[PDB]
Image (tube, rainbow, N blue to C red):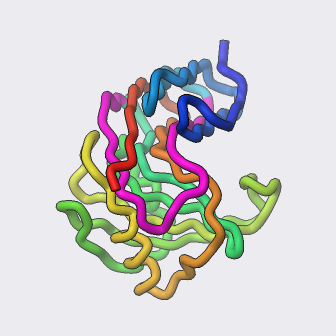
């Protein structure tokens, strides 16, 4: 009995939950910075807790249980407007690297690991502002983990040094769990430690 799409405030944190309706799955907001997602096969879904607005430099801690059975990722995720950008700082992932179809921009060292940087463009696709064209910025951790601190400003400075624009107006900034035609479970707690 799939939880309906929702976004807004819970216990002082912003959250977003969306699915394409094809998979059975339950999204629950728990106390404080915690959320839980249980999902089956059949569709595309993404949900998590965080802040609105995001900042170019926030120190975000996360911890918990992350158990994908197939294609999935755990990342700091969010959007800017002017320009329209969807960005991903990927800390862990299942069977496939979500940035494999993007242009390689080199590496950066952040929070104890090398991260591979990338950029892609999506044309006429679903976004926070309806069907639009937007750029996607990627930073993917080489040493996968399920707990730790992410200094987002390490990634936004790396993207800026690579030529990308990072002066957009921020929308939300969450620690999101995504599943893509595969089943899984996750229970994650986030916090701002800056």
Residue 27 in picture, x, y percent from top left: 56, 23
Give above or below for 26 relative to 117. above
**In the visual, does 185 lie left or right of 14?**
left
Quadrant hosting residue 33:
top left
Magenta part of the protein: which range? 43-67
Residue found at the very far right of the displayed protein:
130
Q: Residue at x 38, y 78 (%)?
A: 158
In the rendered image, the quadrant that contains the C terminus is: bottom left
What secondary structure characterizes most of the magenta part? strand
Residue at the (60%, 61%) spot, across then down: 86
Q: Which residue is nearer to you in this view: 154 or 124?
A: 154
For residue 2, which quarter of the picture? top right
Residue at the (28%, 40%) spot, across then down: 146
- Judging depth in this view, the residue of 171 and 84 nearest the camera is 171
> Is any part of residue 95 visible from this angle?
no
Q: Is residue 90 magenta?
A: no
Q: Is residue 53 left or right of residue 139?
A: right
* On screen, residue 125 above or below 72: below
State which quadrant residue 135 falls in: bottom right
Where residue 103 sits in the image (x, y, percent)?
Answer: 48, 75
Q: Give the side of residue 93 with respect to residue 169, left or right.
A: left
- Provide residue 140's location: percent of width, then percent of height: 36, 60
In the image shown, does 112 or 98 lie closer to the viewer?
A: 112
Q: Quadrant of the N terminus?
A: top right
| Residue 107 visible in the current orientation | yes
- What residue sits 60% from the left and 51% below the top? 52
Q: Is 48 in the magenta?
A: yes
Residue 19 locus on image (x, y percent) = 66, 33
Task: Decide: is 20 above or below 92.
Answer: above
């Amino acid at each position: 009995g799939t939880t309906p799409n929702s976004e807004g405030w819970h216990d002082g944190y912003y959250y977003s939950w969306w699915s394409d309706g094809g998979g059975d799955s339950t999204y629950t907001n728990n106390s404080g910075g915690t959320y839980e997602i249980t999902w089956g096969n059949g569709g595309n879904l993404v949900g998590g807790k965080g802040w609105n607005p995001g900042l170019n430099a926030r120190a975000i801690h996360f911890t918990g249980v992350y158990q994908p059975n197939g294609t999935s990722y755990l990342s700091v995720y969010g959007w800017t407007r002017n320009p329209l950008v969807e960005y991903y700082i990927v800390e862990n992932f299942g069977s496939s690297n979500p940035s494999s179809g993007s242009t390689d921009l080199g590496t950066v060292s952040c929070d104890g690991s090398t991260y591979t940087l990338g950029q892609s463009t999506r044309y006429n696709a679903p976004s926070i502002d309806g069907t639009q064209t937007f750029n996607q910025y990627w930073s993917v951790r080489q040493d996968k983990r399920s707990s730790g601190t992410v200094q987002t400003g390490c990634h936004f400075d790396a993207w800026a040094s690579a030529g990308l624009n990072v002066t957009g107006d921020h929308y939300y900034q969450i620690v999101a769990t995504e599943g893509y035609f595969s089943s899984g479970y996750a229970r994650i707690t986030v916090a701002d430690v800056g």
